[PDB]
Image (cartoon, coloured by chain):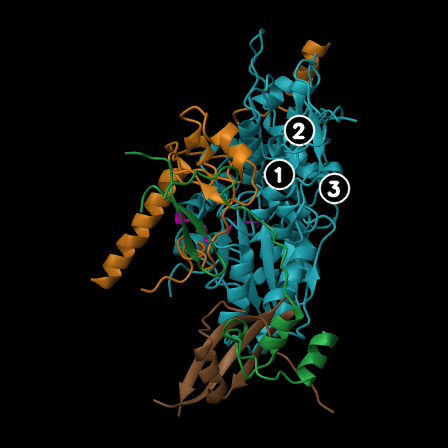
Chain colours: A orange, B green, C brown, D cyan
């Protein structure tokens, strides 16, 4: 029963290859996987190619123009362990901490390779 | 220089050299506990010090030179009210 | 019988204008309940320069 | 008393099918292809007919018939079907495409539609901000080849919600959205989304839940049970709020008079004073700890992360990206654009201030409206009247906006796309209408 409970929905929620909702003609094209990282690069090089073709057109609304400018106010500094206010930064490994106990039991005896995932949160590596 | 024990004031920017630490390679000990210490102090000030300061004709050098020179009465009235 | 009016808060703009000799300085002040910009005379601007006031001071 | 966190329960009742007798071929159909949830429904109704997340998978049987086309709400039937669920969204864009028309055919079958030679219903569709040309091109190709639809429009969800909440169409206001992966700030002037001064922030609900995942993984490296994404989004939903003022609230969050109130313990499912120790307060709160009993090894504490995670939309620096927070971009929009000297506000600036609207699915967190009103009173000149509006369910407003554009008005036929117009012009086209994207250049 339970082994057929999903299968009943399977024979209720099926659609054949001659699809009713699709058109009479298909002519289905082939496409690459086309991951979202390279789409930014193709859009950037298309915009740059159109720019240098028009040069040898001011952009108004592109994906690289609605994207936010950097801040002008200096960023607040925090301890990376507890999220408290950061007073000190250890010179050996460059991690901000709050006070003495967090320093002595976190920042000093920690294993290498933990620092790069601690600084990945604010992207400082 | 390196090897020095310094007390730093953030608000007024005063640098005080307490001395050099224990490194043979005067002599004081390295401080313990927290770096950014918040300390309280208990102040004592006489009435005469405030009477000299609140008299605008002379500064606080009259407490050491001794030329206070006939401090008036209205300044004393202001000190006594305050 | 006297009155006391006081402006204090965050300095957000120090724009002085001339006409070597300044004409007036427009200073914008900011507090926790809003901002308020003011026009000021160069005599006061001399004391502002004496007090070493830049952008971001109270 | 500790609370246990489990997976959300599976839906016992499967989603139904609309009756084929009541289907109208001439009635338009509105689809919101949201990143987190997919919103669909006919124009004639106002309540959402089909609400289900945009995810799907494939099943394997012993008996080998290959009859499994499970999409969305029928993945809420067992843990095994839900665990291998794949979504069509990779980042802010869509990369795979076969699963997209599979999802759309599931939607069209569950809408109770019996078409011929394609769907004879015009499509109302929602699309993102400053979308790349490939996405618009293959959207054009996918609908106007696979579905043979006469008419389609493009529009943004934030401007759709703004058209929902003031249906005259020529108002002026500021709309801020908190989407699943992006935070957008758009100024609207005379009903036109001014896209040359809109701004985008690369943070959303998904990145916040992943931030909580990384933080709680880095807080307790010896947790024996590995937690899923779903338990994470529910403790992000249940136990997170926006602080009134961050600088004072972090300064006393581990204080003993405060830690007894806002410390939330979380129990994982399974079958020399400590009071002066700031580390022990940060780990296990105001209670003493013994690591030998089995119960508190499966325990998880939330003290500073209640307000640390929702703060990052106001300061993106702890999130990692070097962008300004919505305070600063709202401030520079209100104070150094549309003809505004700092100190003197134009009538457009005052009218945008009087009609600030905040939408988005990630606005469900408490304390957003109080914070935004407080800081808008902060940076503005004194005496300026600030009004901020809120929805009860801000994930419904965009679909209601396109439904308002369809049913409420007759000038929806201004923005439609004809098939013959597509064939005479081509994929490279954009309608410069008041409520969607604009041309990439001038």
Question: Which corner quadrant of the image does residue D284 belong to?
Answer: top right
At numbered mark 2, what does the secondary structure look like: helix, strand or loop? Answer: loop
Point out residue D341 in the picture as x, y percentages from the top left corner.
50, 77
The answer to whether D94 appears left or right of D310 in the picture is left
The answer to whether C49 appears left or right of D396 in the picture is left
D169 or B5: nearer the eye?
A: B5
Q: Is residue D257 magenta?
A: no
Q: Which residue is mark 3?
A: D257
Q: Which residue is mark 1?
A: D305
Quick one: label 1 or label 3, which is nearer the N terminus?
3
Point out residue A55 in the picture as x, y percentages from the top left corner.
23, 63
Q: CA distance from mark 3 to mark 2?
A: 17 Å
Q: How many marks?
A: 3
- Chain on which label 2 sits: D
Q: Which residue is mark 2?
A: D273
**Overall secondary structure of the magenta stretch?**
loop
In contact (CB < 8 Å): disc 1 and disc 3: no
Q: Quadrant of the C terminus of chain D?
A: bottom left
Question: In the image, which residues are magenta?
Answer: D124-133
**Residue at image x 41%, y 34%?**
A27
């Amino acid at each position: 029963e339970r082994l057929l409970f999903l299968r009943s929905v399977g024979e209720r929620n099926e659609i054949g290859f001659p699809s009713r909702f699709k058109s009479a003609h298909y002519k289905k094209p082939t496409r690459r996987h086309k991951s979202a990282r390279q789409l930014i690069s193709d859009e950037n090089k298309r915009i740059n190619a159109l720019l240098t073709k028009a040069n040898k057109l001011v952009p108004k609304a592109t994906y690289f123009s609605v994207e936010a400018p950097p801040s002008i106010r200096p960023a607040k500094k925090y301890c990376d362990v507890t999220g408290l206010k950061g007073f000190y930064k250890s010179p050996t490994n460059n991690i901000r901490y709050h006070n003495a106990e967090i320093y002595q039991l976190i920042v000093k005896p920690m294993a290498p390779g933990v620092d790069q995932e601690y600084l990945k949160l604010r992207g400082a590596n | 220089l390196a090897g020095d024990v310094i007390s730093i004031d953030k608000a007024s920017g005063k640098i005080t050299k307490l001395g050099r630490s224990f490194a043979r390679s005067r002599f004081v000990q390295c401080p313990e506990g927290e770096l950014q210490k918040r300390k309280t102090v208990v102040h004592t000030v006489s009435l005469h010090e405030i009477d000299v300061i609140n008299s605008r004709t002379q500064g606080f050098l009259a407490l050491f030179t001794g030329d206070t020179g006939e401090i008036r009465s209205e300044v004393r009235d202001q000190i006594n009210t305050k | 019988k006297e009155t006391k009016e006081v402006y204090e808060g965050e300095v957000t703009e120090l724009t002085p204008e001339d006409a070597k000799t300044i004409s007036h300085v427009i200073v914008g002040l900011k507090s926790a309940k809003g901002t308020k910009t003011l026009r000021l005379d160069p005599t006061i601007y001399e004391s502002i320069q004496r007090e070493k006031v830049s952008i971001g001071d109270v | 008393k500790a609370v246990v966190i489990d997976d959300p329960p599976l839906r016992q009742t499967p989603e139904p099918f609309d009756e084929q007798s009541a289907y109208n071929p001439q009635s338009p159909i509105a689809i919101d292809f949201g990143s987190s949830k997919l919103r669909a429904g006919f124009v004639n109704h106002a309540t959402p007919t089909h609400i289900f997340p945009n995810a799907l998978t494939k099943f394997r049987d012993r008996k080998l018939n290959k009859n499994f086309t499970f999409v969305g709400n029928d993945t809420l039937l067992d843990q095994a079907v839900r665990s291998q669920s794949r979504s069509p969204f990779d980042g802010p864009f869509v990369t795979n495409w076969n699963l997209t028309e599979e999802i759309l055919d599931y939607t069209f079958h569950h809408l109770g539609v019996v078409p011929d030679n394609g769907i004879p219903n015009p499509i109302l569709l929602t699309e993102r901000l400053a979308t790349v040309q490939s996405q618009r091109t293959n959207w054009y190709q996918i609908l106007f080849e696979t579905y043979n639809v006469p008419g389609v429009t493009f529009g943004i969800d934030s401007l759709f919600s703004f058209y929902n909440y003031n249906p005259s169409g020529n108002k002026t206001g500021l709309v801020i959205s908190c989407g699943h992966e992006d935070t957008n700030v758009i100024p609207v002037v005379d009903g036109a989304g001014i896209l040359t001064d809109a701004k985008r922030i690369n943070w959303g609900g998904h990145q916040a839940v992943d931030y909580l995942n990384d933080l709680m993984a880095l807080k307790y490296p010896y947790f024996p049970t590995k937690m899923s994404y779903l338990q994470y989004e529910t403790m992000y939903k249940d136990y997170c709020y926006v602080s009134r003022n961050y600088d004072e609230d972090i300064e006393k969050i581990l204080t003993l008079e405060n830690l007894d109130t806002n410390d939330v313990v979380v129990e994982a499912p399974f079958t020399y004073d400590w009071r002066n120790s700031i580390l022990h307060l940060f780990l296990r709160g105001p209670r003493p700890h013994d690591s030998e009993n089995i119960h508190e090894q499966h325990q998880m504490h939330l003290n500073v992360e209640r307000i640390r995670v929702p703060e990052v939309i106001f300061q993106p620096t702890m999130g990692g990206q070097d962008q300004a927070g919505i305070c600063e971009l709202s401030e520079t929009i209100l104070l150094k654009k549309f003809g505004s000297q700092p100190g003197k506000l134009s009538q457009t600036s005052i009218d945008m201030v009087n009609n600030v609207l905040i939408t988005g699915g990630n606005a469900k967190v408490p304390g957003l409206k109080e914070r935004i009103v407080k800081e808008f009173t902060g940076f503005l000149p004194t005496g300026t009247n600030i009004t901020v509006n809120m929805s009860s369910d801000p994930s419904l407003d965009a679909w209601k906006g396109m439904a308002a554009l369809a049913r409420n008005e007759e000038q929806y036929r201004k923005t439609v796309i004809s098939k013959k117009e597509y064939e005479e012009y081509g994929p490279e086209y954009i309608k410069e209408h008041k409520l969607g994207n604009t041309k990439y250049f001038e």
